[PDB]
Image: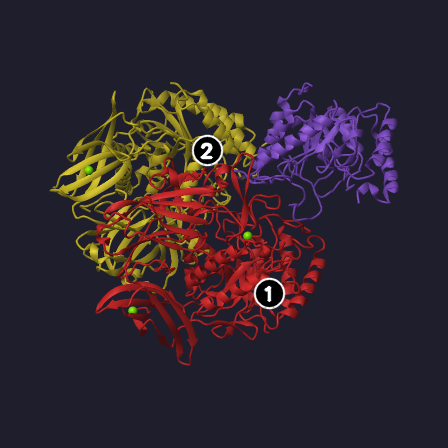
Chain colours: A red, B purple, C yellow
Amino acid sequence: AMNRSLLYPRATTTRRLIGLDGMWRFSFDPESKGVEAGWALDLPSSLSMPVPASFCDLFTDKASREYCGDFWYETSFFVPAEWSGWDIVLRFGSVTHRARVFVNGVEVAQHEGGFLPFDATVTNIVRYNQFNKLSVLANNELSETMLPAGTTCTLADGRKIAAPYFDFYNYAGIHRPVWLMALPKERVLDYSTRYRLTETGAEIDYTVSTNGPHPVTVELYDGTTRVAESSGTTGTLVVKNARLWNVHAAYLYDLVIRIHEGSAVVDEYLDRIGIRTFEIRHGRFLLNGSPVYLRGFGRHEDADIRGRGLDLPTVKRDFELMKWIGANCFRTSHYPYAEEIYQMADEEGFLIIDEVPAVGFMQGFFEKETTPALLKNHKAALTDMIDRDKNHPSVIAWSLLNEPQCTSAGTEEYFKPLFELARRLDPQKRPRTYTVLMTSLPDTSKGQRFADFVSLNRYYGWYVLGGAGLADAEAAFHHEMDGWAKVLHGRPLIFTEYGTDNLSGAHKLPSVMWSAEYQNEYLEMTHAVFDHYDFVQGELVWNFADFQTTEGILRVDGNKKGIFTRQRQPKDAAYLFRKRWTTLPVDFKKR
Amino acid sequence: RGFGRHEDADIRGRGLDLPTVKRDFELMKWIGANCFRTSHYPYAEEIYQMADEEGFLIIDEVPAVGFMQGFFEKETTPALLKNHKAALTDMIDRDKNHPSVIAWSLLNEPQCTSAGTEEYFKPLFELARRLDPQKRPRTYTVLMTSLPDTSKGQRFADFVSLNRYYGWYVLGGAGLADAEAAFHHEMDGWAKVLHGRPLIFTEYGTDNLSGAHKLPSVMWSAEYQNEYLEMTHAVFDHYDFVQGELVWNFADFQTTEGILRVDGNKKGIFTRQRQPKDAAYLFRKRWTTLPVDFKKR
Amino acid sequence: AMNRSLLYPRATTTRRLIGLDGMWRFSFDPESKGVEAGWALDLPSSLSMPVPASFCDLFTDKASREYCGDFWYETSFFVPAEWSGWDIVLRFGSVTHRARVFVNGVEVAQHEGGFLPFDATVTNIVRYNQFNKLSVLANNELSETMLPAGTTCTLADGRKIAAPYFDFYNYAGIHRPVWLMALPKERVLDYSTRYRLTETGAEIDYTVSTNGPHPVTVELYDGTTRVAESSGTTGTLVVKNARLWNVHAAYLYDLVIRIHEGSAVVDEYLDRIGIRTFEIRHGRFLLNGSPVYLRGFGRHEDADIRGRGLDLPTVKRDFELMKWIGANCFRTSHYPYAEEIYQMADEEGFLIIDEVPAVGFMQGFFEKETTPALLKNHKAALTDMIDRDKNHPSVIAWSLLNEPQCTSAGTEEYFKPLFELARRLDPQKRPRTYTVLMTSLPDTSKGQRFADFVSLNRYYGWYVLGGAGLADAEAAFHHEMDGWAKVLHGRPLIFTEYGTDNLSGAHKLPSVMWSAEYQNEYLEMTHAVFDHYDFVQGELVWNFADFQTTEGILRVDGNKKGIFTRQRQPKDAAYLFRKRWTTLPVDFKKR
Ligand SMILES: [Mg+2]
Ligand SMILES: [Mg+2]
Ligand SMILES: [Mg+2]
Ligand SMILES: [Mg+2]
C-alpha cells in the first residue's frame, strides 16, 4: 500500500529471502463457500499441486482442466525467531487472475490481474519461530472489465466455463515464484534510471524512492571495481569509458543502493543495469545512436504440462533457440512475462516490446457502459508493468493493447489517457505502440494516430485470400500498405503478427494450406512485401512456438503457427528465418 | 452400418484403382460394415460389381450436391433440374440390376428450406419412382440448418437421412453435454414428423489426425473422436426409428485448400493410405456386436 | 563425515532452510585446468545455466550436448549475520556423476555417484553477513568402476565422448535442488522405523541417531492430536486405532523428533511416515497382511529440455497418469530418484522398488581386475540409498543390479556381500531383487539364487523371435518360464521389463513391428504367458514414457517403448493397460 514496491526480491546485506515454491495443497471451490466455511484456516479436502504452474494440464479429466471459478492454494511457512523486528512480506510473482491472501486465517492482501506481482505485509500477523498458514483464494473467471477480456458461460450441468475473447487458453493458477522476505522497516521501494552517452563515456541519472528520511547512496560496480558513486536520492552516475549494452552484446553493471543511519547500513538493494539509449529518430529504431531492424517473435508463456508456469530450463532453451535463429527482439504477447525472462534478455542482449494484457477488446467495444471500469484496470496494469520493468536494458518499447476494436466509437477517449500515462510513467520515454487488428485499416483506424510506431498483425494469405490465390493476397497486401504509407508521416512500422498454421512433417508438393511448403511460400511472399517499403523496420512473426488455445475446429490441439514445436524443436520455417535473419544486416532497411 | 465414401486416393484423384477397391472392401468387411452411400456421385461400375460379390448394400447417389434468395428460387433452376433429371435417369438405368443397390439418394444437403423446394423435389422423386422397376426407397440427405419443422423437402423422402455434427460444427469442445441435449431436442422433432418412416444418419464425425492423442481430449484428438462417437451413438440408440448409421467418412480425402482443412478432410475412419485410425476399432467392436436386425421397432 | 546425514532438508523450530535453485554460471573445462588456473575463485568465462537441470539438451550444438569431461557450476549465496553459531551446511540432492565443491576457493567436499545426496559443511569457511562463492567442479566421464558403468572414447578431433554400457543417455549436470542450511551443532542425523500391526492398532519401533549426548523425544501427530510419544533414542510408539497406509489409500502421520537441553529445544526434525508392513510370505507380496499383485512401470527421470532435472509439474502429471491407468507400483530404473518423487508416492499410496545405479555390468564382467573397486562404489551407493529411503512407506523392495552378466564367473563372490549388506542396512528387512538379463537362464544364472523374488527383463516377440513369428516367441517364452518354475522354490517372480518400440500414430493392419497394432498384439500374448503361471506376482512394463538414449540406428530419437509419450500423453497401449490394470483385483493371482 504505502510501501508498494515492484522490485525483484533480493537477498542483500539487510534483506532476507526464502523461496516458497514447491508442492502446495489445492482445492476447487465450486460453490464459493470457502471463506464462510473456514477454508482459510484449513482446507477440508485438498490435493497436492506444484507451485509455480498452471493447474489445468496436470489433471486427466476435462472438468478440472476447464474449471472456472474460485480455487484455493495452501501452504505453510516458518518465520524464524531472529526475524523479529524486520518487516515480514510475502511476494507473489503472479496469481491468475485475481487473489485474496490469508495468513493464519486473516485476510492480508487483495490483487486483481493475473500477470504482475504484488506483496502482502504480514509483520503483525505471523507467529515468530513457528509455522504459519498461507491460504490463497484465487479466481479465473473472465469479464469485460479485466485484462485479458472475455466472458464466462454456464454449461447444462451448471459448471462455469471460460469464454475468452482472446485466442490463448485461459491458464490459471500460481504461475511464478512465491517469496518470503524479511525487509528493514525503512527501505528502498523503487528506483529509476535514464541514460545518456557522452564523448568519454556515459551518464546515468537516477532517482531512489524510500519510505523514510535517512540518506541514500548509490554505487556502480564493474566486477570488484567501483566505477561510479553518488550520494542523494537523485543524482548522476558518471561512467568513464562505459561499456555499452548492445544487441547480442550485452554488458551489465552491478548497482548498489544503500540507506544509512550514521555509519550503519539500514537497507541495501542490489540490481544489474545496462547502459544503453533507445529512441525513434529519423524514422528508425536507434539503439545507442545506431539503427536496428527488429527481427524475432511474438511469444507466449506456454509449455507442455505446466501451462504458463515459469520454467528456467525452458527459458534457457528458448533463448538458445532465439540466438541460434538470429532473432534480436520479441514482444511479451499478450501479458507481462515473469521477471526472469527479462533478466535473461538483459544478459543475452535481446530487445523486448513489453505488453500489458489489454487483449480481447473486440455497438463498438469502447461504447460499452463498462468502459470506465475497464480503463481503470488497464491503467493499473500499465502502471505496474512500467514500474516493474522500466530498469531492464532489454525493455525498449511499450505495447498498450493487442488488437483492440480501434474503429469503435470511443476509441480516442480510451486511447488518449492510456498513451499519456505511458509517457508520464517512463523516465526513459520509450516509444509506445499497440497492435492493429486486420479490420482496422489506415483510413478507418481511430487509434493509429496515438502510436509512436505502428504494429500490424496481418494474415494476407492465411485468414484472408488463402490458398491457390496467393498472388491475390499479395496485391491486397500491397494495397493496404500503400494506405499505411500515407498515414505514417515518418513513423516506423513493424509487423507483430503473421504466419500460417503448419504441422511438423506435413509436406505436400505442390503446397496446401497447413503444409511446410505453404508456410515457406507464404513467408517468402510476406517478406517480399515487407522488403518493398522503407518504413517497415521490424518483423516479429507469430509465434515462437506452438501453444495452447481453447478447443475449436480451427485449432489442431492449440495454435500451430509456431516456428518451433511446443517441445522446442525447429520446424522447417525456422531454417528460412535463420538464413534470412542472420543474413540481414543489423541496420537493414535504410530509410 | 457403414460409411459415406469417396472415389479418392493418393496420386490418382478419383481414378479407378482395383487394388484400392479390393483393399477398401477388405477393410469394410473387417470393420463389420454392411452398407455405404456413393457420396456424392455415382461410382465406377466396378465398385458395385464388387459389392455384388461381397454382399454389401449401396445407397446410390446422384451428384446433386452444392445446392446451397433461396437456392431453388434462382432463375437457373429449370436448367439445373433438367441436368438433375438426366443424371438421375442415367444413374438408375446404369445401376438398377445390381443386387447391392437398395436405395436412391437424390440430393446431398440441398437448401430444402428454400422457397421452391417442393416444385423442385416433386418431379425428381416421381422420376425416381417411375425409373426403378424394383421401386426401391428414395431419400436425400438433410442439411443441419433444415429442421424437422422447417424442411420443405423431408416429406418427399421414403426414409430420412440426416447429416448431423452435434459436438463438432455445433456446440463442440468442453460442452459435449450441451451438444447431446441439443441433439436429443432435434430428434424429438424428427420423431414427430417421421410417421413410421425409418431415419438413418448419413454423416457424422470429427476431424482427427492419426496419432493425435490428448488426455483429457481436445477437438482433433483420437480421444475426442471416440468421446464424440460414444455420445452420438447413445443418441442414435435411444430412438427406435433410427435404423442406420453411415459415418463420415470411410477414409481421409482431398478437399479444396482452407484454414479448416488440414490437407483435405480428416474425418476418415481409415487414413487415405487405408490404415485404421483409433476410431476404426470402436466401430469394429460396435458393428460386429450389434445384431444384423438391431433396433426392433 | 562424522555428521553424515541423508535426511531430507527441513525448516524446523531449530533449522533454517534456503533453496539455491535458479540461474547459475557454467563453464566447460575441456583442458581440465580449472583448479590450477583459479576457476574456483572466479570462472574466467561462463554461460548462464538453470539448476536443477541436465546441461545437455539446453544447447543447440552437438559438441555441448555430448560434452564429456570436467565442467563447472558457480553461484553466490548470502550467509546472514544472525546464523553465527549455527552449523552452515550445503546440501546437493545430486551432482552427476562426481563433484568437488569449493566455497570461497577452498575445497569442502568430494562426492562420487550421480544420483544420491551429499552435504558440505562450510561453517568455518563462509563470511558472515556477506556473499559467498559456491563453485562445483563436476565430471561425467564413465568407467568400469562406477555406477552406472561404461567407458569414454576419444574422437578424431580429440573430444572425449561417453560410451555407456547402458541404454539411457548420459545426462549430467546438477539434477536436483541445492540447499543452504543452518543447523544446530548438536542435531539429529538419522532415524529408523519398523512397523507392527496389533489387534487394537499398530506399534512403531524407532531409533534416533544424534551427534551428541542430550536426550531425545519422539512424538507422532495426526493433525493437531498427538497420538503417541516416547522419550529416548530408541523406543516404541503405540498408535491405537492406527490408520494404515495402503495402496492408493495412503495415510501419513507427522513425526516430531526433538533434542532437549533442560527445557530448551536444541534440535527438531520433522517428517511424515506411513504405518504399513510389507513382506513376502506364502509366495505373495503382503502389504498389511494382504496380497498385492504389482502392476506399473519401469520409469526414468527424463523429460524434454531438462534431461534428468527434477520438475514437480512433470512429477504431478506422471502420478496423475499412473493413477489414471491403474498402476500401483514402479521401479526407480536405473538409479535412485529425487526424494520428491518418493514423497509423492508416499502421499498417493504407490509402491516403489528402489534401485541403485548398478547397471551396465555387461572374460566375464565379474572376473575383471577392477571388480573390487566397483564393489566398493556399489556398496556405498547401496548404503546411501537405503539410508536415504528406508523411512518411506512407499518403498517396499530393493533392486541391487539391473541386468548384470550373472552367468559370469565371479558372480557369487560379487552378489553375496551385496545382498548381505542390503539385509543388514534395512531395519524393515524388505525383500531384495535384481533384474535378470535375457541371456541369463534359469539353469545358467549364478545370481538368481540370492534374490528374495526374481525380476525378469524379457522381450520375447521384440528382440527375440519378433515379427510374423509371434507364436514361436510365445512357445520359447513358455519354455523358459517352465525353467523358472523349477528354480523358484516358492519365491514370487515379477517382470520388470517388456514391451516394443512403437511410434504414436503408427497404425498398420495387419501389424508390423513398430506399429500400435503390434504393441497391442505383443502385450496380449505376453500377458497370457504371465497369467498362465501362479508364481508371476507382478508386471512392470518398460517404460512409463518415451525417453532419451544415445544415438543409434536402433533408437528413433531415443527409446520408444513408452506407454505414454515423452510429453506425457497416452499411446494406444495406455488404454490396454488401463482396462487390464483396473479390472484385475488388487490380490490377483492366488497362489
Ligand atoms: Mg494468442
Ligand atoms: Mg551504495
Ligand atoms: Mg534404459
Ligand atoms: Mg518430540
Q: Which of marks 2 and 1 is in front?
A: 1
Answer with left or right where residue C137 lies relative to residue C161. Answer: left
Q: Which of C192 and A387 is in front in this view?
A: A387
Q: Quadrant of residue C245?
A: top left
Q: Which of C180 and A131 is in front in this view?
A: A131
Q: Is mark 2 on a helix, strand or loop?
A: helix
- For label 2, the crowd category at 10 Å Cα-Cα, with few meaning under 14, some 14 to 19 and many 20 or more, is some
Q: Nearer the viewer, residue A575 or C449?
A: A575
Query: Which label number is shown at residue C324?
Result: 2
| Vertical arrangement, residue B197 with respect to residue A220, above or below | above
Label 1 CB, ligand 1: below 8 Å? no
Q: Mark 1 lies on which chain?
A: A
Q: Which amino acid does label 1 sit on?
A: Gln
| Vertical arrangement, residue A224 with respect to residue B120, above or below | below
Circles 2 and 1 in contact, beta carbons < 8 Å: no
Label 2 CB, ligand 3: below 8 Å? no
Q: What element carries label 1?
A: helix
For ligand 2, the image quadrant comes to bottom left
Q: Distance between the residues labelled 2 and 1?
A: 52 Å
Q: Mark 2 lies on which chain?
A: C
Q: Which amino acid does label 2 sit on?
A: Trp
Residue, disc 1: A448
Badge 2 and badge 1 in a common chain:
no
Q: Quadrant of residue C332?
A: top left
Q: Which residue lies furthest to the front in this view?
A: A369
| Residue B99 visible in the shown view | yes
- For label 1, the crowd category at 10 Å Cα-Cα, with few meaning under 14, some 14 to 19 and many 20 or more, is many
Taking the spot 72% from the left edge, 55% from the top edge, the residue there is: A469
Percent x, y of residue B269: 64, 34
Percent x, y of residue C472: 52, 26
